[PDB]
Length: 287
Ligand SMILES: O[C@H]1[C@H](O)[C@@H](O)[C@H](O)[C@@H](O)[C@H]1O
Ligand SMILES: [Cl-]
Ligand SMILES: [Mg+2]
Ligand SMILES: [Mg+2]
Ligand SMILES: [Mg+2]
Ligand code: NA
Image (cartoon, rainbow, N blue to C red; front, side, top):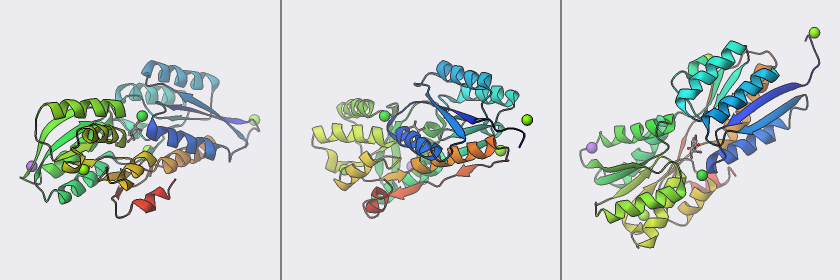
C-alpha cells in the first residue's frame, strides 16, 4: 500500500423510516469492525437536493467509497454519474433505479420477487377469487413500480382475481389508515388489501379494526418488520415478505470497505422470503 491514512466512507441514507432504521443500525454495527475507517452516516431526509449535497461533500473530501440509498430514481443517475466521474467507488444500497449497473455494486433485493411471493400467497388464500385493493408505496420508487407489477402478474394469471382499487399511501402507516378509511367509505367490495410495505398494511389494519371488518379481508405487506410480525402473531396480518435489513446494511458496509481497499467488488442480491403464520417464529428470531 502507498499510504497509512485513515480511510473514510461516506453514507447517505434516504431517510430513517421503519425498515431503513434497521438497515442503518446494521451498517453502524458492521462499521465498528473497521478501526482503520471513519464513517460519515448522513440522512437525506427524503430530499434529493440534500442527498446530492451530501454526495458532493463526500467527493470534495475525497472519501474512499460512498454508499447511497437513493431518494429517487432520477437524481440517482446524476449521483452515480458524478461519483463515477470523481473516480470514487459507489455502492447502491436497497433502492435500485434504471442505470444502477453504472454503479460499482448493488446490495439489496429484487423487488418484483417480493410482489410475486406476496400475491402468490394471497391468491392461494383466496382460492384465486377476489377483489384486490393494492396500496402503492412512494410513487416512482422502483420498489413501488415493481412490487405492484409482481402483484399484477399474479393477478393476471387468474380470471377470478381483479384489481378493484389502487392508490398510494406513500409507504406510510398513517396514510395507509387514511386510504383504507376512504376505500371503506366508497362501498367497494374488497377481499384483500395488498400493500407494497408493512407500514401501509399496518395502517389498513387499524382502519379495518375500527369498523370490525378485519376478519372479512386478507391483509398483506412486505418487509417482515418486527411490527409486522407482531401483527401476524396477533392474527391481524395474513402475509408478509422478509426483506433482510441487517444483511443489506452489513453487506453494504463490507462491500464499501473492500472497494475502499482497492478490491473489485460485486453485487449482493439477498433473497426475499415469504412469511406466513406457519413460519413466523423463524423470522422473529432474525431480530
Ligand atoms: O424506504 C423503503 C421502505 O423502508 C420500505 O418499507 C422498504 O420495503 C423499501 O425497501 C425501502 O426502500
Ligand atoms: Cl415509516
Ligand atoms: Mg504514498
Ligand atoms: Mg457492476
Ligand atoms: Mg383479516
Ligand atoms: Na385476473
